[PDB]
Amino acid sequence: GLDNELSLVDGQDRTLTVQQWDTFLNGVFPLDRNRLTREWFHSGRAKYIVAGPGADEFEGTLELGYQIGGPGIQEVATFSVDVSGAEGGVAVSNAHGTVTGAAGGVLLRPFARLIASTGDSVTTYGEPWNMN
Amino acid sequence: GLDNELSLVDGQDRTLTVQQWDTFLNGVFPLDRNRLTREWFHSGRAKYIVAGPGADEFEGTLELGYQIGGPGIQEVATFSVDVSGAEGGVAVSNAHGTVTGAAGGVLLRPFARLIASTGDSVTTYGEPWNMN
Amino acid sequence: GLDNELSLVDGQDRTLTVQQWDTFLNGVFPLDRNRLTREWFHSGRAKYIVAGPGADEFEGTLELGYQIGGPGIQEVATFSVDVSGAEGGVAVSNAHGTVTGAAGGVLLRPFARLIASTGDSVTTYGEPWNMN
Amino acid sequence: GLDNELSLVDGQDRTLTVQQWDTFLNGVFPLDRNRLTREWFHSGRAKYIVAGPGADEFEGTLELGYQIGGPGIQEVATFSVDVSGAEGGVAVSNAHGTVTGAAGGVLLRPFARLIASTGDSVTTYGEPWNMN
Amino acid sequence: GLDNELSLVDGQDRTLTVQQWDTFLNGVFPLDRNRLTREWFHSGRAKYIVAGPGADEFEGTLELGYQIGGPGIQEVATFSVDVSGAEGGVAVSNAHGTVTGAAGGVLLRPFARLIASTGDSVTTYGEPWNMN
Amino acid sequence: GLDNELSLVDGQDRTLTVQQWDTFLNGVFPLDRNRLTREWFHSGRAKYIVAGPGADEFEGTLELGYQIGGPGIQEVATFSVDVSGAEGGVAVSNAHGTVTGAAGGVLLRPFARLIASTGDSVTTYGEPWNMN
Amino acid sequence: GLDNELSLVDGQDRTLTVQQWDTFLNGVFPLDRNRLTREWFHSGRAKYIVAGPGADEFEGTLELGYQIGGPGIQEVATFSVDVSGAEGGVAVSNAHGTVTGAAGGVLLRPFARLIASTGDSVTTYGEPWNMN
Amino acid sequence: GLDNELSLVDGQDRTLTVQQWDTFLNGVFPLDRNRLTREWFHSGRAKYIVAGPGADEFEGTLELGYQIGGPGIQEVATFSVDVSGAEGGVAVSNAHGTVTGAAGGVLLRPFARLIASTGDSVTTYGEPWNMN
């Protein structure tokens, strides 16, 4: 269910909330049979909520992915999507991810993000999953 | 026939399914006569289904391909295509595939995919074939 | 005449055919006078046939070409063209080809492909020609 | 609360203000476990005010971000957005930053900026945060 | 007069003919005074004729030039133009050609080509001239 | 106040004036702590005036900035904007500027520039600021 | 006066002439004052005439320039312009040319070209000027 | 005042005149403080006049600038602008020019240019200014 959430009061007195549900980063033995290589499958669900003046008429983007820490830090957006209304969620099952040159372990920071067409944004973070 | 399938209850309470059907990964002698080269052709069929609120008005995309595990991990989309309606599925005969630098064998993971215009996606993966 | 053909029943219950006619791959003495160069001319004809529910309302694409095997494996589409209606076909006399770096031997794999705008496709292959 | 602010009387006798609120530069352990990487999270509120003739008909861009100082000087705009009217503001929570090759210590100079469609720009700055 | 010509029975039973008249490849001492350079001037005539159903309303392209062979095999198109009608033809006087690195001779292969808006194509070549 | 100005009688008998006001080049110890780096903040006002026939219908561009002198000479326009009519001007406070490989010293030459839609232009220069 | 000319019976029985009048290639002592450099000023006129069917409705393009023979053979088009009517001409005075790396001397072959919108072209050539 | 002019009787019996007025090329102490470096300011006026049939009907380009002679020959167009009418002219005060690798002296050849939409051009030249 609910893994983590965070709310923020935007610069128009709306209470923006974003949520990270049912996160599962499933590691697998690499298709390339290389010890340096990490492969896994991202599953999970982002939801958002908005309370306050003009909630029912909302215009933002909703995101879900993670950061990879190995040969640096890069961010993967598994999906990134235009939403409207004061509520909603989007779910993913078996997104494919991989990275190589992985010298001694690979950590994965899962996030959920809400971005308003008004520029505002809030993002919630769960605890990293260790890919080794 | 039915090789594999998977379901996701999506973010609007639509039960999304995707099926992988009649897959053949045909390994043949390479046209370039190099021992380092694999050549297959891809055959098979993806099917999707969606029950729930608004099933006969679903918009998304249907894909089918495989991952190449050898010189590294790369995903190949044999086809990728905008669908509509509660059901349907597109089938492929004799895609061409090939790869070189194939230092000892080459593995292949075939996947079928349902992604919706609402951001949600599900992918069904089958068991790898070993070109070698 | 008819060199080869294949048939695929597509995901909307149409019996899709593809034929490959009159093929010639005229190999010739290289204009660069290089022993490592191969120079050739494609001639041939693609045609196709759709039957079953909704045939006179078909949108897809037809192709004719070859893979080149030797320096690597590379696909050349001598022609690639939009098509509509239940039958069609197109022809080529003296298309031009040349490759170099050729470590002795160039094999040639001639094909005809009908692709469907509904994402489906079928492709007929003939027996490789030897350019040396 | 309010961290810093600055006001410019621009080229058409509007007194343009810009403000920087609630600033957290949250330093954390680098996901890549690398001693030469720095990783943080930016959180902040940006506002502007315009007084004077035609204030209610002001067009411009509002921005929040920082400068990174270590491997050189770079500017990062956490956000940058169009604005209309004489008041406005936008807030960001948990934006992710990172930089590497960080040869002893990293400093972060945070700003809020207001640029007018008439070419005028005022930018306010805080005291640098130290990422080590 | 007529050097050569070829006919093709295209995908719609139009008899496509293409012609090449009055060819001259005028080789001359290179403006750079270099042993390794070949310079010349290209003269010739391209003609076509279409026979059968839908002829007098024909859509295609007409081309004239040659292949160069020395440091590789490269096609030059002295002209390429759209045409309509069952008949037509365009001529060229003193086109300019050069190539360098001409490590011992350069051969030139002249062609007239006709291509149809229907995908079908026919091309007639003459025997190579020897710029040396 | 006014730092400097210059005027031109342009090719259509209008007297173009440009002016540079309240220039400040705020040199500060650099954020990268690097002895070859220079960092500063630019603040300033540009104004123009057009006299003569058709003055209330003048169209041009107004620019303000500086040349950087050390690693070479490079021009930076802090801003560049389309203006209309006989009068106007724009202002900038705390714009950010930096440059590295400053092998001993950097000199900064400040300017304001008036460019007319008719191609004409006048540019006034201040005395160089020594960023060391 | 007239330096050179050439006519061609084009592909629609029109009689197309192109002419070259008053050529001058004035060699100067080069501005860089490097003796590998050649520098010059080009002057000339190009005229055309089109007799026969539909002459007064002729649509073409008119070019004039020279080839450079030294580091290789480059084409320079001093001008290239849409002409129309059975008659026309355009003149150039004092165009700049330069080439460097020129290993003892440079030769220049001046040309006048007439290309027609129907794809036909003719081009006349004068005897080369030696630029040393 | 007038530095130089040239006239040309053009392809349509228009006498085209270009003139160069008030030219100043002002060398200064390089801002980069490098004795390999030249830096200057360009000031000047270009004017044109046309007489003959259709003079009020004239469209062209008017340009002013100079060639640089030093690390090579390069032409700088200080302004280049579309004109209409039998008379016109545009002026520039203080344009900035700089060049480096000035391996001893730098000559600047200033020019003014009249280019007709009909293809024709005339360009008047001054005596070079020596940049050291």
Image: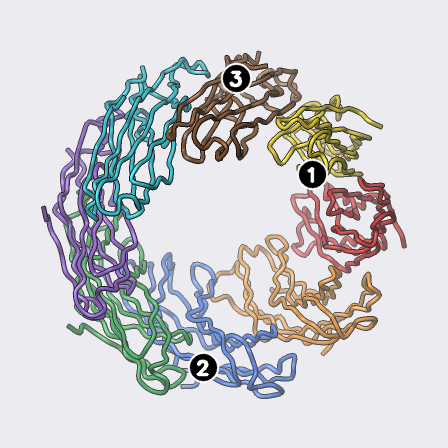
Chain colours: A orange, B blue, C green, D red, E purple, F yellow, G cyan, H brown
Alpha carbon separation for disc pair 1 and 2: 65 Å
Q: Residue at label 3?
A: H108
User: Looking at the image, which residue sits at the far right?
Assistant: D1
Same-chain check, marks 1 and 2: no
Q: Tell me the quadrant of the picture where the C terminus of chain H can be found.
A: top right
Kind of residue sitting beneath label 3: Leu
Tell me if residue H121 comes above or below residue D121 in the rendering: above
Of circles 1 and 2, the one toward us is 1
The answer to which quarter of the image holds residue B24 is: bottom left
The answer to which quarter of the image holds residue C59 is: bottom left
Q: Are marks 1 and 2 in contact (CB under 8 Å)?
A: no
Give the percent coordinates (x, y) of residue A5: 76, 70
> What residue is shown at x 25% (from left), y 24% (from top)?
G2
Q: Residue at label 2?
A: B89
Give the percent coordinates (x, y) of residue E104: 18, 33
Q: Are marks 3 and 1 in contact (CB under 8 Å)?
A: no
Q: Residues within 10 Å of mark 2 (few under 14, many from 20)?
A: many
Kind of residue sitting beneath label 1: Glu
Residue F100 in the figure: left or right of residue C105: right
Residue closer to the observer: C7 or D32: C7
Q: Residue at label 1?
A: F57
Residue E97 visible? The answer is no
Alpha carbon separation for disc pair 2 and 3: 72 Å
Same-chain check, marks 3 and 1: no
Element at label 2: loop
